[PDB]
Image (cartoon, rainbow over all chains, first blue to last red):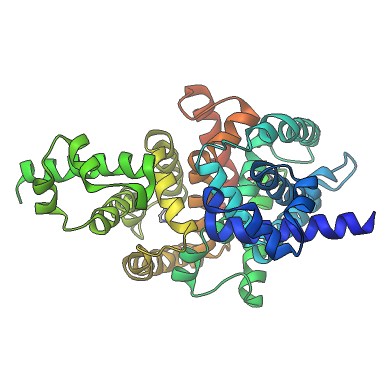
Length: 201
Length: 202
Ligand SMILES: O=c1cc[nH]c(=O)[nH]1
Ligand SMILES: O=c1cc[nH]c(=O)[nH]1
């Protein structure tokens, strides 16, 4: 149904903005229900608790973050695939900083509510894609870097510009919404990581 | 300068770090910091006039630890060797002081309400100075053409990740930086990507 999806997205977006501004414990479901334009009973049909909504919000940003990596295939040009991956991750930092910070804040608390996804569906995908990239490496299409550590570096360097945005602005005077700085950021992150994993000699 | 006094101020700062780490800034009471440091409230207020002053002192101390290697950069150093220590020291700090990494990251997530003066002032000054130093290394052919500030941010981001995102690292790999073998694999992998990413080539 389109209507169910339209409504689930209105709730998730209202939920993101409310968790972002009031934190998990200070947020009440009725407040989210007011801003999505729906009744509490209607909201609870799709998300039975504050915990369910919160987890769903973080699953949504994870699905966005991982889409490029889920699309990886063995016959891709490895360096080209990874440079596109880096570019998509920084567009997410520019456009969805609130969700990036919400995820980072969950990690800082020990991932009390997200540990089910990290040990389950997330670990399954990274195991699968790590084996794929290890194939690219055991075949000389990439230098020898270990796959899980290359992935962590991609995540860390692109999410930095959202999560650490106040420090980036303080040192450079710019943000990712400044077109020129955005393009300089993409090119420089790409240069270091790509040349760092490019086959040699 | 008196060391006993310095030893006492560091004892207080360390009690503050772990109390701020466990209860957050607004939930922390000065009485808790004093009781856990082994000192009277009055002795704490002698050195730190407010909870906000102490909190800022705690975050400045972790900044000083983090930036010491970069302050030590000088034009005549071997660039790649210097950046290899920097990465190694940053990963040692993520292993030994994860609580401080998390507290600083949490300050950034709130918009840096209390620390923004330190970022726009002393931090920006150092990064300007050392970024020009690194631009000199590139204009003298000792490094590939990279932009200095983004190289620095990547050193920070990739090394602090293993502390701030430790639960995700453990979930995906089963390990932490306290495992000697995983620590050494991490150093070698981060160093390899950044160093080979910036090596002159030619
Ligand atoms: O892109 C991603 C995906 C999963 N976890 C992260 O921290 N970043
Ligand atoms: O090492 C450092 C120094 C300043 N700010 C950071 O995030 N990391």
